[PDB]
Image (cartoon, coloured by chain):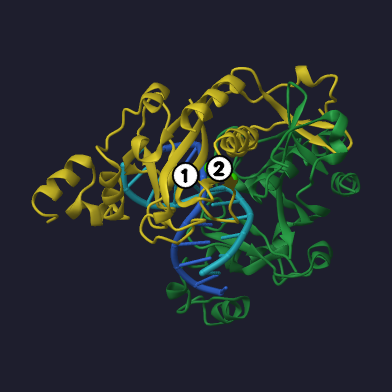
Chain colours: A green, B yellow, C blue, D cyan
Amino acid sequence: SLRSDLINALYDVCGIISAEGKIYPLGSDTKVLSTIFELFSRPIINKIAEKHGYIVEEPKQQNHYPDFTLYKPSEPNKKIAIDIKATYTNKIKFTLGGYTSFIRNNTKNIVYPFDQYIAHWIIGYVYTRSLKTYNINELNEIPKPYKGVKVFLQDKWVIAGDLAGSGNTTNIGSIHAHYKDFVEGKGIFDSEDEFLDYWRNYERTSQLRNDKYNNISEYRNWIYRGRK
Amino acid sequence: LRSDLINALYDENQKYDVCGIISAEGKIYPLGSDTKVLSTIFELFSRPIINKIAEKHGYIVEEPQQNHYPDFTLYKPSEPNKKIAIDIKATYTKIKFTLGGYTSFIRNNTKNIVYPFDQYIAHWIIGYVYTRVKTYNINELNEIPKPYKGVKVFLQDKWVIAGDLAGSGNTTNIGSIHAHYKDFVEGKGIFDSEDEFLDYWRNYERTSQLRNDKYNNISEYRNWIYRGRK
DNA sequence: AAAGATATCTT
DNA sequence: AAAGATATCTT
Ligand SMILES: [Ca+2]
Ligand SMILES: [Ca+2]
């Protein structure tokens, strides 16, 4: 299938190269990598989609989820969203998007209405942590600022957690497990419906959550009480 | 340092473009449409120059560790106490920049800054201004499609191009003047001094409400000051 | 944790 | 505007 091939396809940057052949090495910022990984998945996401007859689309306008929207023109409401993410192993975790945007307002901050996607994949890259230029002839001497990239493709609701991944930028956090857990799909939600209900009703600050729920158990008890 | 720094950036930029990332196996990947990527790609490009010019003048240059301003710190070991902060920025085409938070180091000397705020005597913004616009190989490189066009660069003191409105809400950022690239190079800002910059941003409220009674702009700040900050 | 930094875009 | 999205990271 589209999913199996993609996973199959997905299984080392030297730096930015300028049109004059000079190569600037990467820096220590963890920022540079997340984007680097998108650039690396791009060709693959595309060759596989095409092979399967999907069209790929990236956001045109800013502040929009997801990195890649795959779909057939024939099946407009069976859209697939793919989001590239990465973090360094130091048990790993991810921020998985806002809980106050599109999941609460179907058309807020998403390239296509949320009800139009029937899958939300996360391709996660996991990795391990000279100020001069080089030429192609000396690629072998350029310092890599990370090693052991490992990746997995996995449905989002599956690895989603019950703790927010950020504060002022209200992000859903993922489970705080081992790479094998994301791959294997060991999560905490019974279903996607639960995943969504939990995050659609999550409050922003603890102060508002203490009177409602702050974890999956408390939420389930919250349902029992009558969502009151 | 300053004059040398810009001459270098001006010349190299008017003669060099980034085409994409390159792998350990020679495979070149074209850049993306992500605006946010460019702000870092220009940083990488700038590192060699900065290090080089700084080296001529006897400055040691340092980068931080996660969530710490600034991108580059320059100081002479014989004069550690006089640091130069350099923050790379970038944006597309009037232009506006977000110039960092107004609740970290400007209010608390050591919060989210590589060295105490009071150890720096200059904070320079090197701004990159551009216009928005397969797996390649070196011998193809010249014809790889870029996502920007007409990159310009200025080097200016931060307090100079700093504005009197927030550059962000939830993340409490200082916003620059919303002006043309020329006003940035010439320094046609709104603050009279650096202290008027510091004071204004240190007493600025996070919400319109709180400001409603205090001051929401440079004129109001100045009237506020006249009365004795009342 | 849980809140708020880092940084940039947007109505 | 001003406030709240896109992200990821650390206190
Ligand atoms: Ca930096
Ligand atoms: Ca910067």
Q: Secondary structure at mark 1?
A: strand
Q: At 62% across and 63% down in the image, what residue appears?
A: A173
Residue B84, which numbered label?
1
Does B133 sit left or right of B85 as displayed? Answer: right
Query: For this rendering, which residue is in front, A175 or B222?
Result: B222
Furthest-left residue in view? Answer: B227
Is any part of residue B96 visible from this angle? yes
Dot 1: few (<14), some (14–19), or many (≥20) neighbours within 10 Å?
Answer: many
* Same-subunit check for callouts 1 and 2: yes
Marks 1/2: CA distance?
10 Å
Q: State the count of labels.
A: 2
Above or below residue B148? Residue B37 is below
Q: Who's the residue at 68% across and 45% down the image?
A: A27
Protein chain holding label 2: B
Residue displayed at 64% across by 35% down: B41
Quarter in which the C terminus of chain B is drawn: bottom left
- Which residue corresponds to mark 2? B59
Q: Percent x, y for residue A132? A: 71, 36
Chain of the residue that carries numbered disc 1 in the rendered image: B
Q: Secondary structure at mark 2?
A: loop
Q: Position of residue A125 (x, y in %)?
A: 77, 53
Residue at 70% of width from left, 40% of height from top?
A68
Pick out the residue farthest to the front. Answer: B78
Where is B187 relative to A48, above or below?
A: above
The amino acid pointed to by label 2 is: Tyr
* Circles 1 and 2 in contact, beta carbons < 8 Å: yes
Residue B103: image quadrant is bottom left
- The residue carrying pointer 2 sits among few (fewer than 14), some (14 to 19) or many (20 or more) residues within 10 Å by Cα, namely many
Q: Is residue B221 above or below residue A62?
A: below
Residue type, numbered disc 1? Ile
A61 vs A212, nearest the viewer:
A61
